[PDB]
Amino acid sequence: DEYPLHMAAANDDIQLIKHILSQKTLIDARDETGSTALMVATRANNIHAAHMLIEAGADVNAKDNIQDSPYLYAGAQGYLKILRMTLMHGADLKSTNRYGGTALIPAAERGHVETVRTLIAAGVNVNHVNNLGWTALLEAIILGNGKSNYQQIVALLLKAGANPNLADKDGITPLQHARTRGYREIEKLLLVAGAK
Ligand SMILES: [Cl-]
Ligand SMILES: [Cl-]
Ligand SMILES: [Cl-]
Image (cartoon, rainbow, N blue to C red; front, side, top):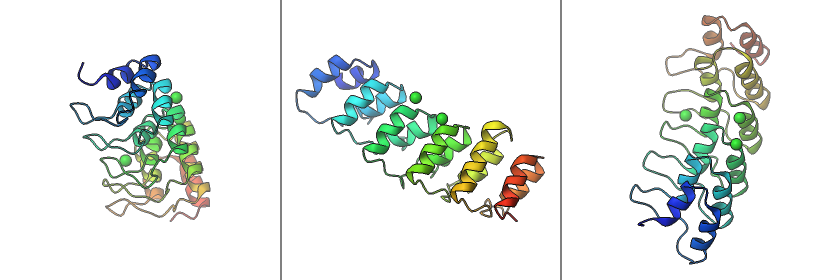
């Protein structure tokens, strides 16, 4: 077919991938959509194919036509095994998705606690503001449900040093957002971090 590495990647077919890679052509060849084979594997959470492609030098920061990269997408989706691989193989922690967010912001949004922990530890900037005017902290409050995972993510962000006073575009602070929603645990965490 036209793009056999991409199909092999979609299928997690690592014997076929091994054979194609032995031909010594460009690992990041684009298919008809502009996607790399590693991007195809990552969208599918095909851990084994992603590992083989990454070890062979596929660029974890190459982008597709919606500004996803393997690193960015694995972080947003909580595909933590692939994400860890990307972090060991050149993830650009300053890179941003189509919303202008780091990988950390969607991980927080979606309540992916261990992905948040991992990204904090790696050094993603906790104070980054996306093109919705939101930080990881703001999204965890506004787009979470105030429970369990989101309390844990708030706590992680604040202990790591996220500024609790970085407000949304309209000047509404994390503290006000928590108060408006009656999120008492998150309010208390914010106040001890110096929120106003
Ligand atoms: Cl996973
Ligand atoms: Cl984002
Ligand atoms: Cl997670």
